Length: 31
Length: 31
Length: 193
Length: 193
Image (cartoon, rainbow over all chains, first blue to last red; front, side, top):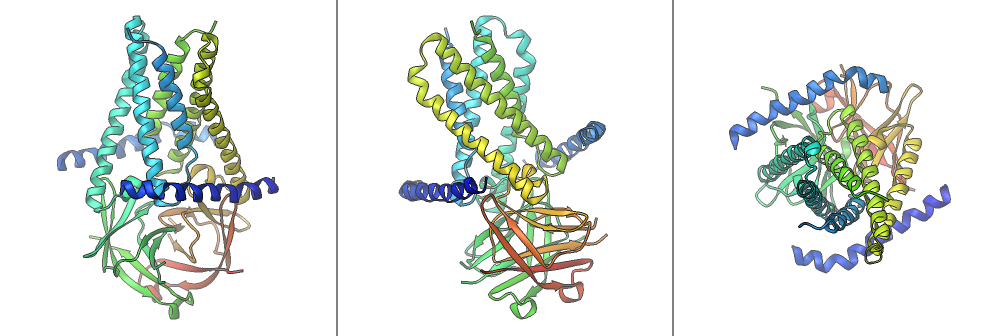
């Protein structure tokens, strides 16, 4: 279970970071 | 809006207090 | 006639949006806004599928064993509409959009000339500690953070839908008092009258 | 083979439970348990209506222009299942049921012989203040309250799904230090490694 948790952590973090990068301009457009 | 705001408060509070009262034994039964 | 397939399309879209709303992390402000927007779309889709299935029942003629259920849905949705109105009024009172972004029961607020601070808070306590970290430079309660724009006030106020409780600044803990470098603690005692 | 009327019944029940879940106040512990149970029932009903409408589409033969949608739902639901597992594991790590009851990103925890404390917390801060009120005697952070059973520890730990950060007790503020009667403040500095 520990290996799966270690895999899951950075994957989730990098997904949300990447989503922020690709949506930065659009979120500026709403503001 | 001021009157209805003062109306809503005690109504919500007393509803949740009553729902706590009538469900005390059942919530004990889960515990 | 009202075709049955729009009910299936609405159910599929509602499932997509509800499942997406279950898994959005609430850490950054844009994620909070995204989660609130997705929840709003979810509620609109739920209203659509409820009303449309009720119309399908009425056009079929089998609505009568479901009148109590649909009336219950409409009553609870009316309550939710009133709750959203109260949330908007809390945003107006706090002079902030944070009551829309956060689901907290209370908001600790104070006014400065350049900023209105509104921090989520869980319950009416007899004291409140505001943590201030320098250079980011921020105010923090319960792990909730607002960017520093100005100093603290001697009086802060905890707002809910129906209550407001005022807190007076009693003590300022510096790094020489606590040992925690680059951090100040402002301690507020609840005003009783 | 599969009647269309069970989809309407499922939609009506899902609407009832979703609308009820929107309006449960999260103040007391039993309300938190009730809200989580209602959310669990909501997710089960959502799974039912999704799978059943997909079966209606397959029995009709019109499933294909919706497969990408339904797969999406299933994929998202899979993630939610994993998330629930992690939440349960957090309950195992915190030795508490509070991660199930609360939606917080972090939980500040410490172990005593008679109790395991687990208080919701929003983010990893450089310091944490635990407020202790005597006689109800309780610990409090961010308005979140745990009933007193024992003393503080010199080290507390903030847990999330993937991280653990340790905090060392640096300072104890008494009423003679702060002026707030019947209240103690325990100040913890984050241990840096």
